[PDB]
Image (cartoon, rainbow, N blue to C red):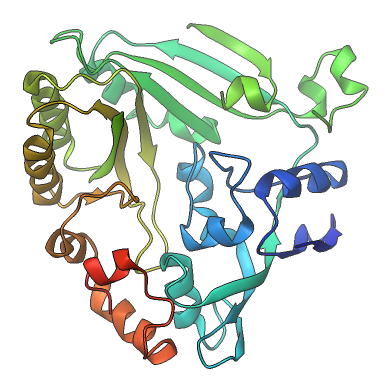
Length: 336
């Protein structure tokens, strides 16, 4: 539950899996290092970050968390401790562990290649659009290459042509060159605008959370989902929009390149019926659902989202035949 080494030269960090990403951030910053993929909470451990293979606002530029793990140590069911690497032997067990939710064993420790930075602040441009078509067109001009971080809040309640209008926030880690004099003293500690310097809390800022992704090319199909959601009467206020980049070698990693949306549906009458249809619609276009604890996602649907599901299940069995690390969700999703 400690951090063993930090090297700015190699950007490598040796850290136990029980260490929270927050604690990792604090320690790594003075060395001019930035955690490659940021957590949603301060209780997210390194092991959780790898097991869930978390993604953030910078996925199009940096991928998910598994992309940055140089090696990890997996305490398996037989009592062994396996040295896992993304490109060496046992790489299959590596990528099955990035995917798996601890169903492969217990991650004890990992080596993580950090992101080099000169400051702890973001420099951001903010834009507002007027409709869903504008929001899409805004992310389709190839301007995503100019910003490492990018996300948008959007209207899912107003009917067209106001549906899909968005407040977009995009930016990158600020250089020392870009900081005001007051902030250059300590650069590495703790809706329309341009060149706005923001710290972590400013930039990165009952219900049923629903997150999915539709392939980039199926844009009209994605628009149709958003339209149908507004029609349904299920109105969410907290809606996040994001365009994902390429995915992993992890067979159970969620992100794929395409349009990613996270809504918070208020628990209403006829929601489970609507969600079931929404699940089918996402899958129909070759999309994928984010499988959380709140799912509410059939095993048939789960196996359909992931083409390499059987390839993963084989690996899980070879490392945990008696299903020691098998949770109730794992059995429910028929992953045994």
